[PDB]
Image 1 (cartoon, one colour):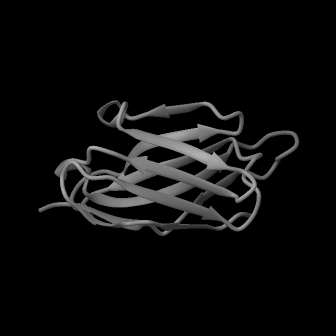
Image 2 (cartoon, helix red, strand yellow; image 1 turned 90 degrees about the vertical axis):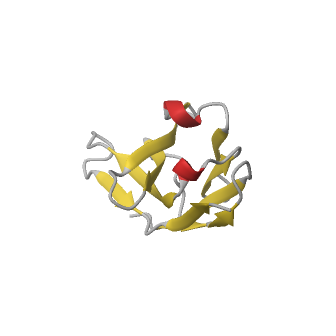
Length: 122
């Protein structure tokens, strides 16, 4: 079972950029979905972006056009490039690996990282 560790968090000015990394302990090329989530104090955890095994991506409406999720299979990495950051993007960002039960993967996969802290503030 893969293990996930996030890095790249920090503080940045509104309008600024950050790049987060989700490092997996092994190949994630076969994982149905790799996701980035975020959670701010007192709020629900929110799905921000995902990339499928086949490379299809989608985005939370509020970040579309300024965030990009991508993957490097040779490095077992998933990245979240964040641009034009707003105070409302402040949160702990966490990655997740999910695969539903299937014939070739009878055991379900649902693994979370511990998170990296993003603060958008002046």
